[PDB]
Every structure is written in structure tokens, then in C-alpha cells.
Length: 140
Ligand SMILES: NC(=O)[C@H]1CC(=O)N(Cc2cccc3c2OCC3)C1
Ligand SMILES: [Zn+2]
Image (tube, rainbow, N blue to C red; front, side):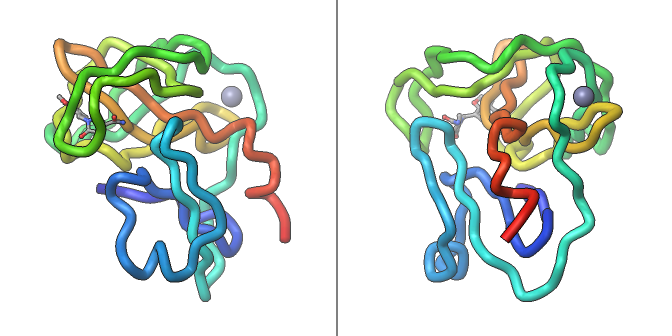
């Protein structure tokens, strides 16, 4: 589990969104595994606006933050899971690292701020849904 809290927005994995998230919906995209809802309180996270390929992510199944090198956001085939059939997921970045299903939502960050959140895993790989292209998270 886990979310990004930036301005009056809550960014979560679409497959983990709650009823309250759907009832306060701002934007959702199944192909990216992302959903954004509105919040009453202002958040403290800042979004990275960069092309970094190194950062650090939080892994709840190890209670640890790991430094990783990660690929550029792209269209990657993801195996079938409890939440989606086998399909191509867009704006996804892969790294070598530990990830179990419940690790989804952990933040990946670089020197500029939050890059994305854990969305996929298995086989000693971890995949992150990029949010650096969602410029509207910084305003309104
Ligand atoms: N974005 C998606 O399609 C995710 C939905 C889901 O439940 N996925 C399975 C998964 C996530 C994280 C780590 C691991 C996984 O499987 C093995 C370890 C992929
Ligand atoms: Zn950066």
C-alpha cells in the first residue's frame, strides 16, 4: 500500500483505490495503473520534473529503502495478476529489486522529488508507474 500526497491530490495504484477515492475522483488510467483523488488537507510530497534514471524506492516487504537504476518510462508486458489480465502497461519503468504484491504504493524518488510508485514485481524485478509527466499535479 502507499500514496503520493501532493497539493490537494492523493495518487494511488488504481488497483488499490478505495470507495472514497472513486467518490472523489480526479483522474484514472487503467493502462498506467494510476488513480488520483482529491483531498481536504494539503500534502507535503513534491513531484520530480526530470529525466533521472537513478533513485531510491521504499520496499514494505523488507522495511527498507533501496537505491536503484531504472529504465525510461515505456510500454512493458506485465504478467496476469489478481487485479489485471496479462497486458501491456504504459509509462512503466523497471529496476532490479525486491517487490511483492503488497509493496505497490511505495515511493520511488530522486534528488528532484517523487518519480513514481511501485506497481509491478516478481523474478527479482520491481516496476514503477511514472508520474513525472503529470504536470497538472503541481497546480489547481
Ligand atoms: N500493475 C499491475 O499490473 C500489478 C497488479 C498486481 O497485482 N500485480 C502483481 C504484482 C505486483 C507487485 C509485485 C509483485 C506482483 O506479482 C509478483 C510480485 C501487478
Ligand atoms: Zn530527478
